[PDB]
Length: 252
Image (tube, rainbow, N blue to C red; front, side, top):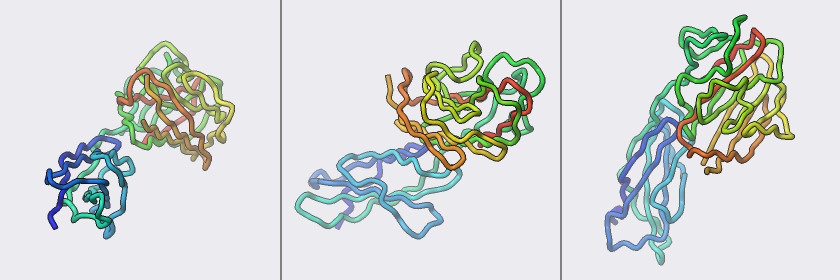
């Protein structure tokens, strides 16, 4: 008849929200907690976590959208859930995905989100402007226009901005090439995705050395695999590389 649990912290990040709750009546003995969320615009809460832990990382949230969260608890001999905490509203933070400006061989759109491979010599991979891929984000690229394909073509994600290599087909990176081949720490997988054409999207979903699970989607097919990284799930760079002119990639 009193809420035994309240939300204690809301940790708003670019790719999700961590909700942490605390038992506010020491005399309550909790078996299970139940966390729900909804968009502030929606008329229905849905369960996102039921279990004995007192925090949960909520990854399926759109940026720029407010969500409401509430939590309750149930005792061991009582089947009925307790009253709910006061609800709390949260949102992910906003860190735009943009390409590096001033990198030879690539021309950018005014908002720095579309990169075109031009006729100039290029020193290597065009990286994001900073490591702005955060775990929990769905990172989406769209291929606007194409050029001649080449074995060193890549689109992907990696730990560090490294100027040496010709592509992201290298250690501490995951990428796809323009033939649909997928590389994990520079090692090509047997399974391929359909090769990109203009209009194709490529999506990366990465969820927690360190063992991450990576889902790459493209042209209505997916591959899923393990990626072992020596960093943690800290923010990652993204990048692309194309040898021949005409390839143009939007990042969302």
